[PDB]
Amino acid sequence: IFDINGEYAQAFTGIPNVKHTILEKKQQKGELYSEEYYCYKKIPYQALGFAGLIKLLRPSDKTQLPALRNALSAINRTHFKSRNIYLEKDDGETFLLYDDCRDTNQSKLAEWLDLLRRRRLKRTNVWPPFKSLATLVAEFGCVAADRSNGSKRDAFGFSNVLPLVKIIQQLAEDIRFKSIVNLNGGGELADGGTHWDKAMSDEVDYFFGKEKGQENDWNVHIVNMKNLAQDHAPMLLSALLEMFAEILFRRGQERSYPTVLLLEEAHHYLRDPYAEIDSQIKAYERLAKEGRKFKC
Amino acid sequence: ETFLLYDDCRDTNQSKLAEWLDLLRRRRLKRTNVWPPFKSLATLVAEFGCSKRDAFGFSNVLPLVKIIQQLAEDIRFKSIVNLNGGGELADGGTHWDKAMSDEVDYFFGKEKGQENDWNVHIVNMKNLAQDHAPMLLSALLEMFAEILFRRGQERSYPTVLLLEEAHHYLRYERLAKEGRKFKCSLIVSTQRPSELSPTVLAMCSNWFSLRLTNERDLQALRYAMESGNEQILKQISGLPRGDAVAFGSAFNLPVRISINQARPGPKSSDAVFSEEW
Amino acid sequence: SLIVSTQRPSELSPTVLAMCSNWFSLRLTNERDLQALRYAMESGNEQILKQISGLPRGDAVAFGSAFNLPVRISINQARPGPKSSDAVFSEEWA
């Protein structure tokens, strides 16, 4: 059941074999079922998705699309520190700089692009801070390298991207959204080289469940909250539909578990009236189509 | 002299790019013997989006390139279209006809005079996404019609087509009209006739109607009759399962026929909720 | 002078059918076509109209300014006739 407003909790007291969640310790038969037995759950900012991040970035200004695409595409093979903007040398020597914005040895961007397309560069195994994406976005577009033995600085591009940088950083500087994200981190990494499979298997196993022949602890998954967002809640609720549709399609007929959903008040969030993009329409249309293929 | 096209709007040697684009316009290059990938068109569009240059002019081409870059990577669409490329190309200016003809000959039977290794061509498409299905199916149908136009009657053979749930993809429209001329036949099966094309229904010469309840479905079907009567429309609303009402050019009077059962039955898979436990 | 041959009176331009001094009508079961014809039908003639909905093969109703009075005509076959192709799929599937 995918609740929206917190009123069904009143009448559902005293039901055996129920897993309860609101927005490790497991109890069982022999203990009464009552209130004030709630848990918490947090969603990170990486789970929104590549298409979701693109939609929230809403690139509709000149040549910002290639910059955003390459900024999002240049995260696994980028060397960056907290406050040290320098270019890693292949030979080994280090020429340190300062925080000042000055053009130095940046002509090797072509070499870095060729090397990262070759897929023989050192990778990054840390959890990227949110401000890293903003730094990468701000970095591209400003510098325009010359053809040979020269440089050119243009303030027109900086003026054009000033609305871009303000709209991307001011909205990210918010407090209403900040109360539902957890930064504890400290997960674990699996070796073998197929870690990309793990990066999706973890959530499809924990949040969605296992396949037949295996054992999962929770059998019902209630989602309910009191805090509501006027312009952000429907997107986040619809954000879960695209990932679920992708998971259901990839599962195939080999693995498929029956699921009964009870989404409520669809017209509030299924079709948002202040948005023009029709991407979500195909998303829930495909989800509805997939509801027929298997037991859903 | 060697030149390469870039990806991230790279500006390199713009003085000699003008002669490159002029030669490309006048076609003074070397022919390629392989099929480029589908993103080659996107790269060409980026190159052609374009002394000093103004970003205002280049800003006009963002929607198509962003749509292409947001649609190509999807597994659902990539599961259907083959983007391997690199196919062998013949020398000349009739490459399109060969590529069309190969697929048409393989999929929709062969030309008159050539023996075939089959007589029934069953096609299973249950995983195809209906968001992209109608355009592909309509394109295939119109390509078949365009190929059939050149064939003529003297080089054609009788063909029969069966289409279940045809209202989804029947929505480009010349196949039905030219079917009589090019010796073709069709069978339309559907469940909501209100969505059927207004012209396609009138062309049909025989009618089989089962239990149909909605007024709008029987409001338009009333409007598109040519050889029926008004004395059987009442029994439509209460037709039992397995009973049909027929009127056309095969019966002197309309007949209430109970259809015989054909063995074996079709693949009707039932999701049992108690066996799986 | 013009001769109009058609099967859908509702698909004709409404101002050209009324200009025709004479008329003909073979079997027509669609009510919307019969109503369109009756919109330009001579008054006082109703019994022959009931045959129009049920005229058998090759029967015509003649009413106009070139006939003494309406009559149900049995048209006679002319030899040779039209092409009458009507391609048959059994003969090529033997």
Image (spheres, coloured by chain):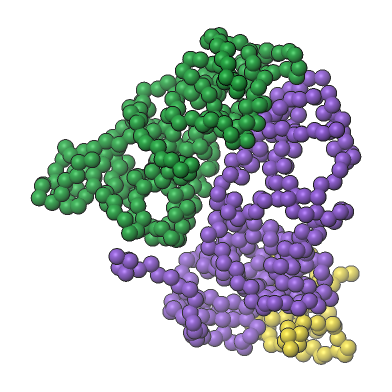
Chain colours: A green, B purple, C yellow
Foreground pick, B112 / B161: B112
**Looking at the image, which residue is at 23% across and 47% down?**
A19
How many marks are shown on the rendered structure?
Answer: 0
Task: Confirm whether residue C47 shows in the render.
Answer: no
**C93 left or right, relative to A65:** right
Quadrant of the drawing holding the C terminus of chain A:
bottom left
- Residue at 51% x, 21% y is A80
Query: Which sits in the foreground, B206 or C9?
Result: B206
Measured as percent of width and height from the top left, residue A62 is found at 65, 27
Going by the image, does C4 lie left or right of B264? right
Q: In this orientation, which residue lies closer to the viewer: B103 or C29?
A: B103
Instruction: Name the spot of residue B265 as percent of width and height, x first.
Output: 48, 79
Residue drawn at 83 percent across, 79 percent down: C66
User: Does the image show residue B212?
Assistant: yes
Residue at image coords 64%, 60%: B137
Q: Give coordinates of residue C60: x percent, y percent.
A: 75, 84
Residue A23 location in percent, x, y? 30, 37
Specify the quadrant of the image occupied by residue A90. Answer: top right
C3 sits left or right of B238 in the view: right
Q: Is residue B260 above or below residue B138?
A: below
